[PDB]
Amino acid sequence: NKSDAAAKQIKKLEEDFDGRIGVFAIDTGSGNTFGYRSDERFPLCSSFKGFLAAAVLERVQQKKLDINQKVKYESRDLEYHSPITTKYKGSGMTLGDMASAALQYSDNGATNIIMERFLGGPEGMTKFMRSIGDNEFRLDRWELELNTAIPGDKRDTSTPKAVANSLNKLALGNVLNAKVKAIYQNWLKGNTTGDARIRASVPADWVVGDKTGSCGAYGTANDYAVIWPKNRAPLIVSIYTTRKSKDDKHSDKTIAEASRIAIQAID
Ligand SMILES: *C(=O)N1C[C@H](NOS(=O)(=O)O)C=C(C)[C@H]1C(N)=O
Ligand SMILES: [Cl-]
Image 1 (cartoon, rainbow, N blue to C red):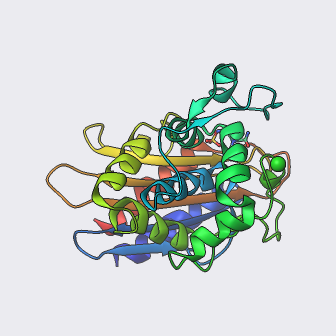
Image 2 (cartoon, rainbow, N blue to C red):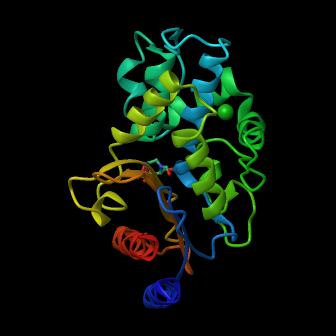
């Protein structure tokens, strides 16, 4: 019933903006799920940086990396949108700071430095995802080439369900031990780019940790969140959108609204 009505609303929403919305949402307290195009592929854009940070933490937990190790790059030409790395260029940053910059600010320099030195590049990032049983995820290119969002291109894509499940594994499951998962969770909660997406869809008193992506082509954008309501179990929401034309702007309000609908369906 509620599921049928939610489906109709997403559909109207995708027609209203001549685009494509994929949704997966889970109420971890009740088991309730909702999916719309949940097994279809969508560009990840910046949203994979949330997982890159999870990979970094797993490496620290396995003791291959130290969270306070210094990462120096004084002579590295930084990629476009390196707001955090560019201010620490002189002195370097700790591993954990760079990784949380990758997540919380979408820092492209942080991203590509981490993939280059600690994670084995895009194939290594893909391998990490495979290792938690995510068969859908792939990253193939570096920042910024990975953001082309060309329709019909499987490169740098995933599905909403796989995103949701993976997040549930990393933020809520036991890939990460209690102490390291707490940190990951805090990184998610302090994300600075998601105010007009999933966070906008929920009472202000609910706690959200999220990671957004905005390819800036084909109107492509997304957000995934763990959500802690008061006196209830966490929710997981995954929202992915594209648009028909290359020049199309992304719509924060469609994302926020698809989130409202996904949440109402599962609650
Ligand atoms: C990632 O997709 N980015 C980085 C930046 N952050 O906004 S986002 O977190 O919503 O993505 C902005 C972008 C337009 C995009 C990029 N530069 O690739
Ligand atoms: Cl590179």
